[PDB]
Each structure stands twice: as structure tokens, then as C-alpha cells.
Image (cartoon, coloured by chain):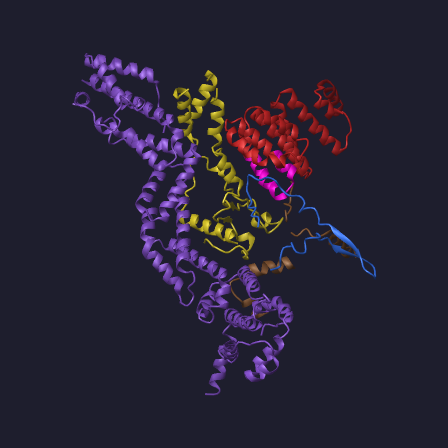
Chain colours: A purple, B brown, C red, D blue, E yellow
Amino acid sequence: QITPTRDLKVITDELQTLSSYIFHTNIVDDLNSLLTWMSPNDAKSNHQLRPPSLRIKNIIKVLFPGNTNKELQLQLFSTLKEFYIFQVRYHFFLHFNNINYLKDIQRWENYYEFPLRYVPIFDVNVNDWALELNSLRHYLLNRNIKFKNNLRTRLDKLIMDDDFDLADNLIQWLKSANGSLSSTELIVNALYSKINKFCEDNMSRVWNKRFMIMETFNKFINQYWSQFSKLVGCPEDDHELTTTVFNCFESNFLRIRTNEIFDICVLAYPDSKVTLLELRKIMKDFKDYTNIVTTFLSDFKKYILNPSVTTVDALLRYVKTIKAFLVLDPTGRCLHSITTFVKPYFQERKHLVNVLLYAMLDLPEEELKEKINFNVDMKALLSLVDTLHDSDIIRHAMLYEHILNYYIAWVPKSSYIK
Amino acid sequence: CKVPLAKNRSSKKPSDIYSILSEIVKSASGRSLKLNAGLIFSEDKRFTHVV
Amino acid sequence: VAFKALEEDDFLKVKQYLLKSESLELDYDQKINLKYLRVKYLVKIGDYDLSMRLINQYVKECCEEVADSNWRFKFEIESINVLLLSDVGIRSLPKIIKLIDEYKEIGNPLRCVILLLKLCEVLIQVGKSMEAECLISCNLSTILEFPFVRKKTDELLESLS
Amino acid sequence: PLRYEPNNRDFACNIIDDLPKLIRFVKDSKRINIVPYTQPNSLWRGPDED
Amino acid sequence: VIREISTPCLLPDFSKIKSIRVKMHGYFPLEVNFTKDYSASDFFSGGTIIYIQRKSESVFENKASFRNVEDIHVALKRKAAESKNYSRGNTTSSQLVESLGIQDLTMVELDTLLSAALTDSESYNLGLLCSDKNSGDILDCQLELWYKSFGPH
């Protein structure tokens, strides 16, 4: 995209000489009047967003109603293009440091292109006017850091507020500019932020539902996928993109549940136990287990291991967590790790042995009250009892078949994890 | 003709004075293959079953 | 003595010593110092076409023959000085950055600070000294801890004024 | 609580952490023993396990 | 017949192999063809392991324009991968150099050079760079020299 420049003075003199020779009339003063009108450098003689008078329009009609005259007109048009190109960049450079927002550039674009409607100089088949404006946009992107940062913030704000049409207008402006801030990174970041907030809004504090990640993914798709596909321009049926979006949703769901696992296991159980089964379908790596247990132990000890908490409720919540994690983890290795971390605190409390064995044998409260000097919560006692009592935790032809069905059908610190 | 082997730039607790000295005096007096094996075969529990 | 002579601008004495260098039998550790001494001397004279071809050969052979990372660092920054001194330090931006983050992990503060000054110096010969002043202001506290860089650090301050 | 987030503009690297931590000499009745150094006020200021 | 396998897999006999190539998003591809002069056995005689060089996602690589296609799916995958580490900001030196506004190596250098002159030899030099057959931020260079030549002063 090489553009030539031949100085303001030279082209002005060339324009004056050509007009004087071709027209043989004193339109040079008028020609000076028009060029000032198209020139944005002088704010007094230009348009100032005002339509021209009859004089300007008539002269344009004269300019735009043999071969030597035709080519002379062609160089005159080329010289006018150079002058207009010269004027716009100089004006743009005069106000280059004054640009801090997108709305500034369109109003300047409108400011520059206001005379363009009244005087046609740009060929329809040649998108020259687009070329230099894209060139200036590319430069503004690649020279003005604060403008680049403002665009990032503006696009992020617009996509947070569901201002989709303007966001699309922003993106086309970016792809037209072809600057160092490619739209692909922006919409990825905008999409990633939007899905996270939507996930935070929807799948927080709710655990009693089943296959709810399907519901949230479906709800989000119905609400924004068409707009997002329009923004990107990719076909609506992009399978791989939807799969990656789904993979991010479940990753977010894993992250939130890890953060909330304490309240999930302590309070919401057993009502949230269904979510635990859904969680069991998701965790696959050792790091996930370690993060879950270290987070769970952190919150548990922060709240439960206070000696200020009643020992009866402490054990009651403790066993509630044990069964919850056992349902979550059939192996029970996490239970062992939780166990090994928590026992010294249990030995710290003194009445734990008596009350627990009495809970084991379901002793009546009267015997408890005879020799125990601290109140024991009866509704806790019944609840722990109910949890404790929860118990949801031909003869020759078959030998040929079973020997094939059992031996050919290939099935693909101690144990302490009973 | 120079088979320059690439030195593995491996890289956390700094510990204390005594622990380091105890370590050195204490030290004074296949794993990769198996680690590969867990990667050479994967995506199933067949190898453990056959062993 | 030669290094002190270089500091006191006694070019005649150091020049005579380099003549002894090429025909002496020297230990490797000694060899590097004289090898490092020569490049520093050539910088002061002003000829950089010879030194630039000379410094790169040294560092290239300072990584294959002997894996001396410390002497590699000292040679690299000399080349950085040669470039920015010739009003073109922008070529060194890829080189300086790759060392910064590399030594951030290592954690040697002296390495981290020296590259900061070089980074500051390149930014001021661009015409963007505004942000260079902003960066140096925040880090001024931790760069005065090292003595021998203070002379360079102080001198840059009057330049900003 | 101080929040000292890592910033590129902060090149003020720390070396005390790289240096090995000091220790203390305390002698009991049986013999002279060696313990890791703790600041006199570190017991109530140390990073909680909790 | 093209045979696609995972990394820790037992390739067939070396003498029957004609070429092998590695392609994956990230590390730039490496493809070697075995002619009659050298067999795979001789190539792997020193060792059965071949090393690959890392590609670089450097800010300096993308001065003004992106030659990279930057597909939406891989970009989303990379952001998700980065967020996984982040879950497990201006903390990177590349952001620092981005904040400094000195990403464009050439544009910065010429701005320093044009600061003042415009000697004929150097003037033709910048013009030669402006009219380069192939380069990057050519329009940026063209538009600076226009600013220097006929801009405010």
C-alpha cells in the first residue's frame, strides 16, 4: 500500500496551473475557496459540518458535467486525490495525541468524509478511500498504546452489557485496521469472560439438580451462541467450538464446586449428594483430588476444629463429611488423608470417646444425663443415630460358556481405606 | 563431529543450617523405564491386570 | 593494574600490556580476563566494528569450549553496551529481555539491576524517556544497594534532572 | 495483611530467602542440642497451620 | 500408507521406513526422509530419541501484522489452557515491553533516526526501506517519513 506525496506547494501550484490552462477563467480564487472547504486544516473556511452554498455545488457541476483534455482531467483528479490525502493525514497528525476512544475516530472519519459526498473524487471500483483510512487505523493501533488499552476496555464493557451491534461494529473496525490487536484474541477473551460470569451467576449455590451442566450450557447457547457466531462470522453449526465451550463450562463447574466443597459436604448433604455423583464423573487427575482435600481440610479446620464449637455437633458434621466423601470417593483414600489430618484434634477433646460409644449403642438420654454434666443436643442425637443406621452404603453347557465368559472376557500404609 | 548432549536444567524449600549438614553426613556413608511404561501404554487398566 | 589503568584512562600502559598478551603462556582464568580486558579497551578507543566481530566470537566460544555462564553474562552485556553506545540499542531489546526473565528466576539481584539500567538507557535514546523516568523512580530504592553501579546510576540522574 | 503481588516493574529480588535459615544453640540437662531458629515473637506471629 | 501413532509407540523395522515427520500445534514441524544413502537404523544408531526445538510466542515476532492465521478454536484452547494454570494481570515481561510501547522494532529505530537534517544518503536509505519488496510495517514506515517530511515542526 504505497502512497505518493508531492508536497503541498507543488501540488497547489500544479492545480492552479492546470485549472488556469484548462478553464482559461478566474476560477483559481474559487478553486482556492473549495480547497479550503475540503481542507480540515483551517476550521474557518472548511465545512464545519455545514452543507456548501450554491457556488461550490455549481463549480463541482462544472468540474463534473479530446483525449488530451481527458488525460489532463485524469491528472487533475490524481492531484486532487494527493491534496486530499495530504490534508487528511496532516490534520490527523495534528490531533493524533488527542485520540482516546473509538467514538473519536468515527467523528473524525465523518469530519474528513463530509466533503466527500458533495464532491466525488474516489472511484467506485477502486476502494482507495478505504485503503488510507485503514492505513491510519493501523497506525493508530500500532502507535497509540493508551488508545489500544481503551479499545480493550470498551470492547470488554460492551460485551458485558450485551451491546452486540456496537461490538460487531468495533470488530469490523478492528479487522479493517489489521493492527497488532487482532480481533480473534479480543473475542476469545470477551467470550471467556462472559461465560465465566454467566457460570458464576447460574451454577452458584445450587446443588440439588441433576445433569444441570447440560441445562446451563443449553441455556447459554440459546441466549448468546447465535450472537457470538454472528460476531465471529463462523457457521452456527461449529461442532468443535461448541465442544470447547462445553469443556470450559465443566472446567468452571469443577472450579466452583471445589471452592464450595465445604458447604456442599457439611450443610447441603445429603441433598447435594446427586451433585457429588456428577462431580465424580468429572475429576480425573491427582491434582484435582489434592486441591479438593487441601481446600476441604482448610475450611473444615477453619470452622469445625474450633474448640468453641460443640463437640457433639463437631462429630456430627464430621461423620456427615465422612459419608459424603465416601459416596464421592469409593476408594476412601481422601477419607484416610482427612482422617490422618484430623485425629489429633479429636484426641484434644475429652468427652468424645464416651459420647461416641454411647451414640454407637443408642443409649437413652436418661442414662446420658445421669453422669454427663454438659447438655447434649437431642435432635443431633437422633440425627446421628439415623445416619449411623443408614444402610445405603444345563450344568455342563454353562461351564463352557462361563469359562469363556469369565476367562476370555478380559476385564480392563496398608489399605486402611475400608 | 560433536554430539553435544543437552544438560537437563532441573530446578524447593531452602531448609535450615543443621538439616543441610545432617543431610550431607548421612549421604556420606528403571524408574524412568517404568515412568515411560505408564506413558507407553495408557488409557486402560490392562497391564496391571496381566501383571 | 591494567583494569585500574583503564579506569584512569591510561591507554598507553594498557596498550603496551596487550602486546605481552599475545605471546605469553597464560592460565585459562587469566586468558579470559585479558580476553575480557581487550574488548573493554577497544570500546574506549571507539572502533566497534572490530570489537563487535570480536565479542561475539568470544561468547560463542564461551559456551561450547567451556560452559562458563558467568563469563557469558559479562560478555553479553558488553555487546549490549557497544550497540546502544552507537545509537542503535534497539537490536539488543530481544537480547536484554530474554536475559531479564531468565535471571528473574535465578534471583541474582545484581544481574537483575544491571539489565534494568541497560533497559533504561535504551529507552532514553529512543525519545521515550518519560516512561523510563517512571520505571526508574519505582526501582530507585533497590538499585542503590549495589555500589559499583551507583556511578552509572548517579550519572543517569542528572541526565533526567 | 499485606498483599505483595508480583509486578514486572518490581525488580527488587529477595536474597534472604535464598540464604539458609539460621539456627539456635540451646543446652538441656543431658547435652547441648541444636534447634531451628525462631524469632522471640515468632511463636504468636508465625504462619498459622490453620 | 500413512500411519498415525502416538508418541511412545513401537515403530516398525528401521530398514523398511522411508520417512518420518512430526507435526503438532506449537513446536514447529520436523520431517526427515530416508534416502538410499542413510537408513533409519544408521540415523538412530546414536540413539532412538530425536529432539525437537520449541517455537516462540514472542511479542517481537508480531511487530505490526500477524502472519499467523490465529484460528478461533486454537485461540480458545490456548486461553483455556492458560486459565487452567492461572486458576491453579501484568506479571509478564512481554506485557512490560508492551506497556513501554516499543513493540515495533523498526518503527522505534527510524523514529530515533529521523529525530533532529535528512542527509541524501540516509534519505535514500529510508526510501529504499519504504519501497522494500517484502517487509512488515511498511505502511507505518511510509507514514512516519511523511510525518517527518511534511508534518508539524
Q: Is residue E34 above or below residue A267?
A: above
**Which of B35 and A128 lies nearest the eye of the viewer?**
A128
Q: In which quarter of the image is residue A152?
A: top left
Residue under the point 24% across and 18% down = A33
* Foreground residue among D39 and B49: D39
Q: Does the magenta stretch include residue D47?
A: no
Q: Quadrant of residue C105?
A: top right
**Left-right relation of A172 to B26:** left
Residue C116 rendering spot, x and y as whole percentages: 59, 34
* Residue placed most toward the observer, A226 or B15: B15
Query: Could you tell me which residue is drawn at 35 percent across and 48 percent down?
Result: A161
Left/right placement of residue E100 relative to residue A53 reads: right
Q: Is A358 rendered above or below residue E68?
A: below
Q: What stretch is highlighted in magenta?
A: C94-114
| Residue D6 shows in this picture | yes
Q: In this view, does A44 lie to the left or right of A287?
A: left
Magenta highlight: main SS: helix
Quadrant the N terminus of chain A occupies: top left
Residue A345's x, y, as percent? 62, 68
**x, y percentage for residue A380?**
51, 76
Number of marks in picture:
0
* Relative image position of residue B28 (x, y in whole percent): 78, 55
User: Please, which residue is most extreme toward the bottom here?
Assistant: A394
Left/right of residue A100 with respect to residue C103 in the rendered view: left
* Residue C96 forms part of the magenta stretch: yes
Image position of A168 with respect to C20: above or below? below
Residue found at the far right of this picture: D30
Inspect this view and state whether residue C22 appears: no
Picture quarter with the C terminus of chain A: bottom right
